[PDB]
Image: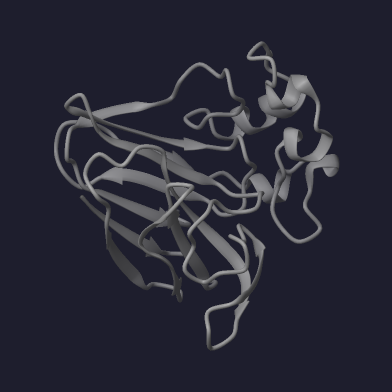
Length: 206
């Protein structure tokens, strides 16, 4: 499956793509404002994620640091990124169907549209100014808007026991982005697409 990753932000981002225990495609790449990076994701990939990283430095070996979304200091991500990260999430070819969503469960750093480029389903978007409106207690000094599990480490925010309800903090993300997951047991905003669809992830779509 092909994912076109487009940076419409006025600032550089370092795109990242991982399924948690391995890179997807090259795993990461710099995207200056306006640049597009097309990656190939193996059919059947379960639990893949694409995200933006901001304010990165990398040396000639591809090692360094990012202020949001850092994946163990690597340009080419093999693991998931450090919150806060707006997440494009997907599982492909699951009994004939693809499943996609956007999630704020690990916070928000960059606005994002996640849309199919092939027929049969709709896209999702979280493009509100979540960082500008972020509750004071959730603001990440390094940049972005942390989720409340990252900040407070409670069973209720992290849904540790598989029982948890919405919270003042989850309702903040949900009010600004109704079509993204705001907490672990949120009413699902997952979109079912035809198996083997292709996609585009656009940072700063508006």
